[PDB]
Amino acid sequence: MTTFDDRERAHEAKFAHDAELNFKAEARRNRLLGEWAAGLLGKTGDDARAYALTVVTSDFDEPGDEDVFRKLAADLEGKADEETIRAKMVELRATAREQIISEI
């Protein structure tokens, strides 16, 4: 009865016309970071998937806020160095578009 159908995806040239399919890769930078911490925290399957679906802010650019580092170094206590957090998510600017163009 419902008014929806969302089906397979079809990104054919869409990354330089459309918003909707662009948007995911346009951002992505923080969407994949719970999918990192998941495994380290022992989360797998839906335990990973659901956890990943509550990890987005895009913190830690210039000093003035800094909470994600503070929270991760507690949550991930024993599984990430300070530098292991602060060096990682730096590069994911590239990995963000990459993982979409991988898992099309």
Image: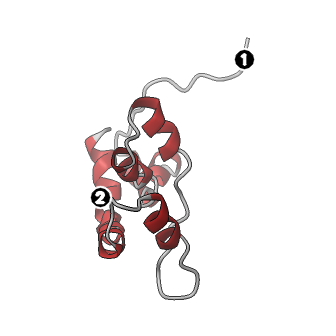
From the viewer's perspective, is 88 left or right of 8? left
| Callout 2 amino acid | Thr
Q: Residue furthest front?
A: 78
| Callout 1 amino acid | Thr
- Residue at 53 percent across and 57 percent down: it is 56
Considering only vertical position in the picture, is 29 above or below 52? below
Q: Name the residue under label 1.
A: 2
- Residue at 48 percent across and 64 percent down: it is 74
Q: Is residue 17 visible?
A: no
Q: Mark 2 or mark 1, which is nearer the start of the sequence?
A: 1
SS for callout 2 = helix
- In the picture, the quarter occupied by the N terminus is top right
Q: Residues within 10 Å of mark 2 (few under 14, many from 20)?
A: some
Q: Residues within 10 Å of mark 1 (few under 14, many from 20)?
A: few
Q: Quadrant of residue 94?
A: bottom left
Q: Quadrant of residue 30?
A: bottom left
Q: Can residue 26 be seen in this view?
A: yes
Q: Mark 2 points at which residue?
A: 95
Q: Where is residue 99 in the image (x, y as percent from the top left)?
A: 30, 48
From the viewer's perspective, is 39 left or right of 30? left
In this view of the protein, which residue sits in the foreground, 16 or 6?
6
Q: Where is residue 50 in the image (x, y as percent from the top left)?
A: 52, 38
- Residue 13 image label: none
SS for callout 1 = loop
Q: Which residue lies furthest to the right in this view?
A: 1
- Residue at 35 percent across and 67 percent down: it is 89
Q: Where is residue 40 in the image (x, y as percent from the top left)?
A: 34, 50
Alpha carbon separation for disc pair 1 and 2: 36 Å
In this view of the protein, which residue sits in the foreground, 36 or 29?
36
Considering only vertical position in the picture, is 61 above or below 42? below
